[PDB]
View 1 (cartoon, helix red, strand yellow):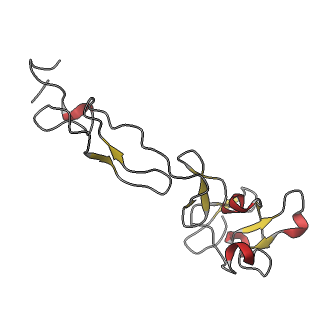
View 2 (view 1 turned 60 degrees about the horizontal axis):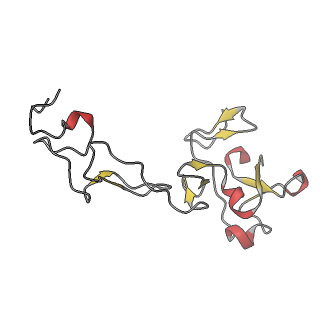
View 3 (view 1 turned 45 degrees about the vertical axis):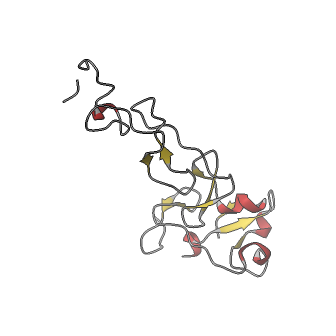
Length: 146
């Protein structure tokens, strides 16, 4: 009902979530992107009909249910990376196991006596859909691999 654009019109909602039904940029205070694990909510800037970027939350912020961490506004890596450790395979295949680097001898679940100083003995399980067993399968809703 706006558009090119008719005279006097600033934009058409089609071009983005920051345009009123009446073809005008929304205020530099309107929300256009819901919050997120790693990203903050998006606000319009009142100058364009596009919804701007979205500032990222601190880096080692938990995401995907304590399963992973936030890296540059993206849920990546593994929760193990928050504490200097590395994810390793532990059935218990969809449990999160960590180890000190280069030392597979140390590979233990998050809810073990060691690691307690980090996970307070909580046995974190991989989210269904996650990779498992050295990228050989994925985790079911049944917590089974492949």
